[PDB]
Length: 49
DNA sequence: CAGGATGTATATATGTGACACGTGCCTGGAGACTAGGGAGTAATCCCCTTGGCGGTTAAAACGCGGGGGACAGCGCGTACGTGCGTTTAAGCGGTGCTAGAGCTGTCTACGACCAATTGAGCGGCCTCGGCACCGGG
Image (cartoon, rainbow, N blue to C red; front, side, top):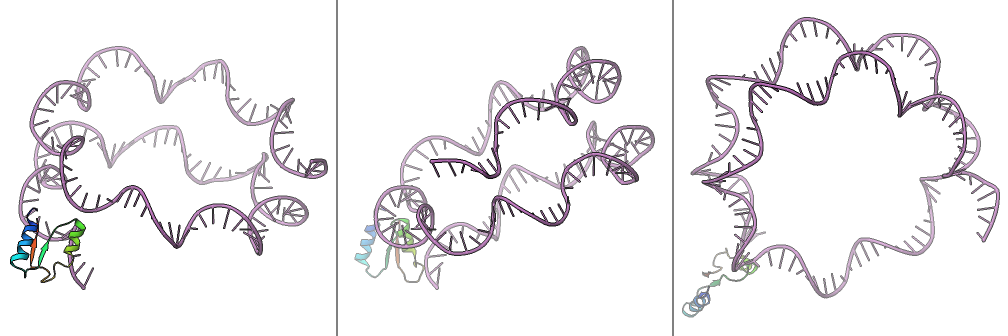
């Protein structure tokens, strides 16, 4: 959990073309983020703890 | 703010229903006295199912606002109560009759009971698939 932001920033820095999805927050926020996440090309790289 | 006009008590009385009280019967009970059985109390002790630690989010809670529901006032209508008269079958108790609940006597098939044998059921274990969970329409 301490390096999720670090990984996200490194991805945004080096490879700007990846759709990054940081899976964090309360349950309700996690459900909101999961809503429609099964669709194709919704995100390219997911970062979780 | 009275008073006929009812209705509801209150008190007394008596004699016929019913508690109340002998008189003896006895047969079903109630207890005493030996002998035999037996299941649960008591002490350990192995083993699960409680009661006790720290987090996570989900539900309880607090507030707000207005909206629809409770409760009170009021009035219209009709039906439900009360009284009077007519009607009916309900209460009484008197007689007649027999049907079967009950007591009784005899004979008997069914079940408790006891011993040996057998497999139906149940704890246990594992593999698996019906539905819990979930995110898009």
